[PDB]
Length: 301
Image (cartoon, rainbow, N blue to C red):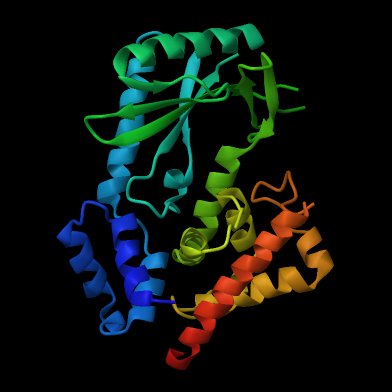
């Protein structure tokens, strides 16, 4: 591994506009990484994307919301995506705008068609091809927003995270239950308990995925669940570099013990991550990447 080249490429991924204030704050907050490429790559791969980029990604979704508020009725607007947990690794991170009905399939079909008309009329780049989401491009800001049509799951008290059901334009039905807000709240809460350490691990693994020459087909959904499964007491006081051996132990334990990997559930606890043999092979390839980083890092621990 060429950590010098990986570090530069990582700078262009998380800071594509090359804002010098971001780079200066990085080396200022981490003076130890100087003249050592492996520490630079690890520290930046765990570092959160600067709010300079995140605020503009959230702002692009806000403009989409205002345009839809000119045509849509009986809906509420929420957001999902890595941006909402600050676990995104790209400065040009897109955002998903959820359009949830306050009240079934015909109401969702109407909101989907009305969203198509308004968004195609506002944004020159508007993709209405996929039956589960509309994708727009704010050419003025250079940001992308996906728009998803859904409603609340309604099947002696109303529980809080009853989930949403995504509208499927292709089948004219509602997709099965998803729990994006519960997942967001659980990730942010546990990261708050560990002073940001959970998000460092998540962003780290996602960057190892993007930089791997192997095809690690593990979604952010899966990477979130893997890190969220780690017990807090194992990394409560660990520094940034010590999170790498902890990720190694977790990934090695998942590949080793068959019941450990069979009991791994999603962050919301409503699905199991590993049922799918290529997914476990992707978990193995991710273990290789962590093992490589760990071996190159242990001399500094």
